[PDB]
Length: 311
Ligand SMILES: N[C@@H](Cc1c[nH]c2ccccc12)C(=O)O
Ligand SMILES: OC[C@H]1O[C@@H](O)[C@H](O)[C@@H](O)[C@@H]1O
Image: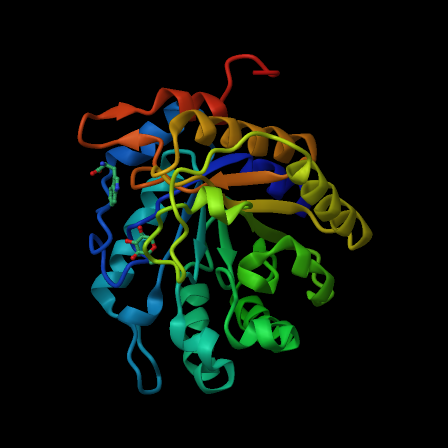
């Protein structure tokens, strides 16, 4: 059942700064086959694969996805699956859809029909995730996302009757917006949120924000993580949905010891609440792996995969 499929997600990592950029490598990470074994042998069971399909799909109906790009996603799905990893395939950045859900609906639903039909025979280790971090007009009216996600789920279910589908709330997948999330009566949904609080710490010096948070911010644990994860767990129990926290992480412009405190505190609380999770992210500015030296960032890796359960 879906609770077991969520438990199977377990510990995971995002292949970020890759296929969710305008093109693969634009944000600094080209995928390599060797990433999959590296990630598996470090203790992760799952790859989350951010994919920004909008850059690669026709603007006019039937909104066909570029065949070469589609073949690259095929390759990632197959290489992860054969090497024993789960893979979450999403729709990631989509500025057009967050800005104008009604105008972009047809194109988004065509994208999901293409993905769903193409991958309908994949095993249960392949998961679909309808839309990363809804924001924009979805923040103004969260019911626009409730209505749209039901339409996208219906499309997926025409070809994938029982595949696990991962759905999050608005406010960029804020757990506080679970209150406004409404889901169909479908027994194979996993609910997701992302956790980056405090943004002033995790995104200090991130230039893709407006405003850009200042650096020099340190962090130590108080009670906010526990309060947040308990709120989310009670929502999940009230609504009988399993939970996957699909992104959490702290940017490299913060001091390393603070990032390690934060990463371990979050991972510990996630696992206390039986939330599966995926770290943001493998190899870039939040990375646990440095491709330049071909070395793990051991303090951060051990905060995710501790050698003893209380470490
Ligand atoms: N310095 C590492 C990791 C890294 C830091 N910032 C990045 C931005 C994009 C991609 C990678 C990175 C590298 O160049 O690989
Ligand atoms: O979201 C846009 C930005 O996201 C960041 O994670 C990436 O590092 C940037 O390269 C990118 O421009």
